[PDB]
Image 1: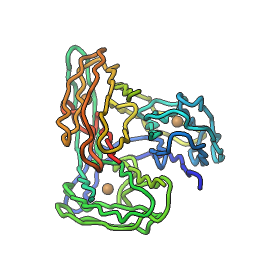
Image 2: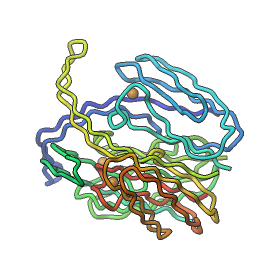
Image 3: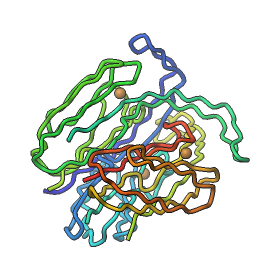
Image 4: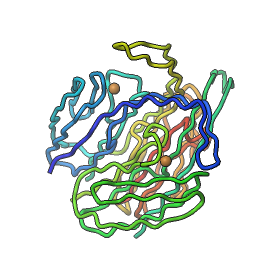
Length: 111
Length: 111
Length: 110
Ligand SMILES: [Cu+2]
Ligand SMILES: [Cu+2]
Ligand SMILES: [Cu+2]
């Protein structure tokens, strides 16, 4: 039917940990991720993306090629619809945060 | 025909390195990556995924929509098969580690 | 026409914060990203990839399965041309930097 994307935030801190004999140290990463990151559609069909923002703050969802640029508030849901009338690969990104904190995804429009 | 995915772990620490005049300082990133992250199939076909675990620890490979939940031991290869009976975009993730340490991928089932 | 990929570097340092009583340890993330990261093409396609390198350093673009392996200088734009003669999923990666700094992408054929 329609796509389902969940936006999650992760605050990871692992000073030291032995995982199956392997010790990992000084890990510190904070990120926001769109799950899933990639969406593939056929050129022409209308797209419906139900974005559920589970992040503690407002998150962005943009796709330049199709004038898509929304802002979903914390704990809110938002259906984003548009028509992929152009072929190619387009970056799905958050216009609100650093791109290497809230990692971008991809909208692929096949011929 | 048959997908090939390699799971790799990276333990990266760079105190300070000047590359072509640009300073790359205080880098500390630990991640596990599925190479490649995205698999694109068509609704209906029988998917075959040969997953080779090059990570020094056990790694997970999960895709809820198709009941896929596997653990690949360090240095082992496991072929994962399932039918993509439904269209859409589904997250490929590890159920053992933090999603922003072991970055997730996507299974795209197209009509 | 063809694919347009922009390569960007992110040098991100964020001091410790306290958001709604919740403390967030200082963050430090340095990455290089291909935007877009994924390319889906039909088998037998004469793929054209215009790669604009916005990174301040040389960036690599490789896809083993098709002999693709180029080095794009900082600020330059290079067009990659090859034919996707094989179906499957192939990693788009940079042979110059650690894979978890410059995150890999994917070339999907059919
Ligand atoms: Cu964001
Ligand atoms: Cu993992
Ligand atoms: Cu690079």
